[PDB]
Image (cartoon, grey):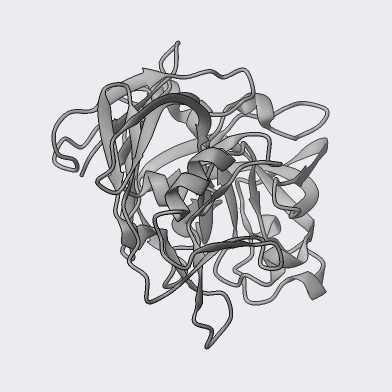
């Protein structure tokens, strides 16, 4: 089998991407944030505290004839950005882009943190990291990809995120028309439950390539590109007027400045992030100070190749017995 779904930026800055997902019988369609950095499929629901729902579409398991309470099961997550949520668990039928899983754990939120309430466009998350990070207790549950894997034509999914435009998540096949050149594959460590890999280095604009190992994760659920302070300092040094602002909490720059591209290495191959991808607009409405899309990972404890980086590539998440990551230009 295969599946193919369009993924759409939630706003004009590509702060996140939503993908429609069919849950239950009859189908309830929710727009979920596909997140290769986490491993829970959780949704706004009829069980969510009323005051914490503000425009989201909810899953109502009582209206799904295929829903079954996973007795005794609870879940609770606190993301790397101070956001959290918790609740109970149902198993139900979940379809993405024509690909159907029966008995998928659907984690129904009783509580969500304010940041989720405040984002009306995101109805929940669909985790695509490794199932070892799933938070369901007492019995950890599998991700949508893990459950689909053996049925797929090939045990892979691909992320093709757009810049200020829709893109595509495919399951079970590689669309050879969606990228240029070849796909370069690179080793993955699953030791922290992430799609974790080592970039071979970077370049700033037309500058010379610096060969250096940068261990980090491919994370569709993180907006920005978080890299070591040395690397980030070297980037913003080439933007006149750019400064790191403690009050804002990162590098900012005047919108009149021209942003250089940023290149990262995948083996001997090179992915070029155009300068425009690194502009995240005024820090506040009407400000001439713009927020940067490349920021320091110091104090995160891990480097994160988020949407800023991934949307410059066609990315293969290969779930073979030994997982690997593939990157192509597009």
Q: Nearer the viewer, residue 55 or 190?
A: 190
Snapshot quadrant of residue 322? top left
Q: With respect to residue 315, does 280 lie above or below?
A: below
The furthest residue to the bottom: 286
- Residue plotted at (68% across, 55% down): 61
Q: Position of residue 245 (x, y in %)?
A: 64, 64
* Res. 112 in view: yes
Please state the horizontal and vertical placement of residue 68, each as a whole percent of the image. Answer: 70, 42
- For the point 46% across and 71% down, which residue is it? 11
Left of 137 or right of it: where is 218? left
Residue 74 in which image quadrant: top right
Would residue 170 be seen by someone viewing this image from the given angle?
Answer: no
Q: Residue furthest top?
A: 321
Quadrant of the image containing the N terminus: top left
Q: Is residue 55 above or below residue 116?
A: below
State the image quarter where residue 268 is shown: top left
Towards the viewer: 330 or 257: 257
* Frontmost residue, 227 versus 118: 227
Q: Residue at x 57, y 19 (%)?
A: 190
Q: Is residue 236 left or right of residue 121?
A: left
Q: In the image, residue 113 lies at what x, y percent?
A: 77, 61
Q: Is residue 209 above or below residue 64?
A: above
In which quadrant will I find the C terminus?
Answer: top left
Looking at the picture, how far across and down is residue 177, in whole percent?
13, 41
Q: How many marks?
A: 0
Q: Nearer the viewer, residue 256 or 185?
A: 256
Say which residue appears at 32% left-offset and 21% top-offset. 267
């Amino acid at each position: 089998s295969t599946g193919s779904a369009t993924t759409t930026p939630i706003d004009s800055l590509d702060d996140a991407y939503i993908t429609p997902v069919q849950i239950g019988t009859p189908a309830q369609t929710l727009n979920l944030d596909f997140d290769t950095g986490s491993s829970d499929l959780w949704v706004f629901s009829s069980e969510t505290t009323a005051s914490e729902v503000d425009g989201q579409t909810i899953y109502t398991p009582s209206k799904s004839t295929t829903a079954k309470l996973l007795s005794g099961a609870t879940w609770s997550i606190s993301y790397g950005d101070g956001s959290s949520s918790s609740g109970d668990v149902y198993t139900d039928t979940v379809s993405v882009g024509g690909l159907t899983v029966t008995g998928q754990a659907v984690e129904s939120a009783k509580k969500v943190s304010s940041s989720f309430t405040e984002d009306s466009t995101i109805d929940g998350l669909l985790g695509l990291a490794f199932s070892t990070l799933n938070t369901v207790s007492p019995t950890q549950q599998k991700t949508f990809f893990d459950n689909a894997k053996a049925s797929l034509d090939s045990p892979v999914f691909t992320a093709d995120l757009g810049y200020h435009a829709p893109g595509t998540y495919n399951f079970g096949f590689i669309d050879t028309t969606a990228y240029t050149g070849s796909i370069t594959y690179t080793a993955v460590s699953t030791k922290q439950g992430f799609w974790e890999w080592t970039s071979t280095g970077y370049a700033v604009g037309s500058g010379t390539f610096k060969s250096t190992s940068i261990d980090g994760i491919a994370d569709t659920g993180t907006t920005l590109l978080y890299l070591p302070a040395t690397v980030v300092s070297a980037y913003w040094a080439q933007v006149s007027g750019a400064k790191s602002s403690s009050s804002v909490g990162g590098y900012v720059f005047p919108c009149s400045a021209t942003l250089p591209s940023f290149t990262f290495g995948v083996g001997s191959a090179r992915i070029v992030i155009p300068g425009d991808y690194i502009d995240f607009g005024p820090i506040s409405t009407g400000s001439s100070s713009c927020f940067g899309g490349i920021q320091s990972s110091a104090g995160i404890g891990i480097n994160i190749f988020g949407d800023v980086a991934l949307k410059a590539a066609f990315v293969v998440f290969n779930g073979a017995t030994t997982p690997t990551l593939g990157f192509a230009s597009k």
